[PDB]
Image 1: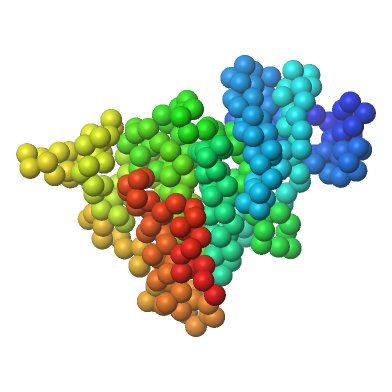
Image 2: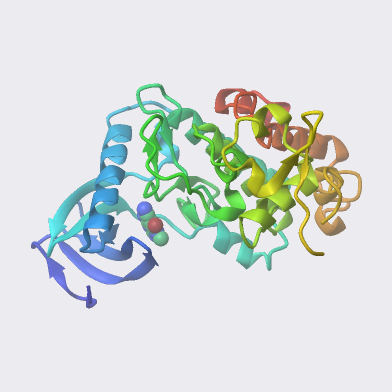
Length: 331
Ligand SMILES: Cn1c(Br)c(C#N)c2c(N)ncnc21
């Protein structure tokens, strides 16, 4: 769909410019003459596949809207939706630039532990809200690009792109999440729950502070190998229940598991998050040496929280309420 700047829709919206594009269609900046404000309009492609998935996205956003609580305001507000020229159109509040752009603006050197903490608190609050029983919504595509600043002057954020999202027990796809942020349970082909978003968050928070993705796999086998470098071989009880365990691992006579090796990774569990964060060495690449709010003690709290978010076991992985009570968030 060609949308000229200046185009008027339904004596209500004046199209200004293209903000964004995706597999789903496009996002435009538009002026709403009724509310007298600028809005972001997500225009879904005129194809059955994209329409049907966007209808689920609208349903989940409307479900979230009807829950007025103090935890709901870290999610982008869907204002309304309509059909226009056979495109489902979703109208959101305007937000600012995304956390990938924030990292690109640091030349991928990362933001402070204090700004990382502010992001972590908001995102944990958002995940607590999605875990509301009557919602039980799995985002399924958390990544820096899907987290937007509310205002370029400020550190408030909201999550966008409920395009892949599903309620617990309403799974469609086995293959979900962006690979760098993909949970071990999804790599392993296991039935997934809200814990996959907490895995993504853990990955995201390390990257926000280092500037670089924690686990930058080139394909699923590389992804799982990069996870094993930092966290070791997944527990046997998980691998024993995983449809895809033998994509990555081999079981021995004594019920132990080991990596499948290919042609020539650091040995399992020897790429320590302790060294990635630079806990005892002035932070990532020693770039935070002597900076306020980047003490060893501050770093150890952060490391502890992240290792709880990166539990292989989705049963025992930290949940949003408990993440919010972690010492990392104490004054
Ligand atoms: C790129 N982008 C997306 Br996706 C939005 C949503 N939802 C959004 C938005 N609401 N404001 C600005 N840019 C945006």
